[PDB]
Image (spheres, coloured by chain):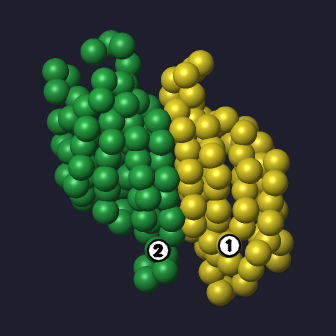
Chain colours: A yellow, B green
Amino acid sequence: SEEPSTVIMREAARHGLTIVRLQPQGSRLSLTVQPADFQALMAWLDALGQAGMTTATLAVTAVAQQPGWVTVNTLVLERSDEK
Amino acid sequence: SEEPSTVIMREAARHGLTIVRLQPQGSRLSLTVQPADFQALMAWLDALGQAGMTTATLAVTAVAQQPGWVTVNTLVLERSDEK
């Protein structure tokens, strides 16, 4: 993975996740993700986990309108020295 | 599930998660969970998800000492009117 930013939006899109903002700040990335399936956002990070990415920050809230969905307050990804 | 507090610690323990603090504040609960497998803490919430519990807040950070593990900053659970 030459472009770490890709895995996020790539895995995001396939999981129906909207990463509005991304920032390749070395290891840590700044991700902005609209309300999501707790499934999708996990599996997406699980997917990024394959990239050597760790959830460096995940900040989240349950939605009142459709329980079982979540609201990502702020999300930071961390990466390996691998790349 | 007459005692919602049980599912959390029950599912916690089976997933190797330490819920130090729990608060049955109606729908929302205050959970304090020591550093965890992102797998375990998800699967535990997935498990609580079976209880009718939503992750009302999940606040988390990646650990520097053993990547792929996470640090739960603050976690709030939300419950159904089912109980």
On residue B63, which mark appears?
A: 2
Identified by mark 2, the residue type is: Val
Residue occupying the point 42% across, 65% down: B71
Counting from the top left corner in percent of width and height, residue B20 is at 22, 55
Counting from the top left corner in percent of width and height, residue B43 is at 38, 47
Residue occupying the point 82% across, 77% down: A2
Q: Quadrant of the C terminus of chain B?
A: top left
Mark 1–mark 2 Cα distance, whole angstroms, equals 12 Å
As helix, strand or loop, the secondary structure at mark 1 comes to strand
Residue occupying the point 36% across, 66% down: B35
Q: Quadrant of the N terminus of chain B?
A: top left
The quarter of the picture where residue A30 lies is: bottom right
* Left or right side of A14 for B33: left
Residue under numbered circle 1: A28
Counting from the top left corner in percent of width and height, residue A23 is at 80, 66
Identified by mark 1, the residue type is: Arg
**Image vertical order of residue B62 relative to residue B55, above or below:** below
Counting from the top left corner in percent of width and height, residue B4 is at 23, 29
As helix, strand or loop, the secondary structure at mark 2 comes to loop
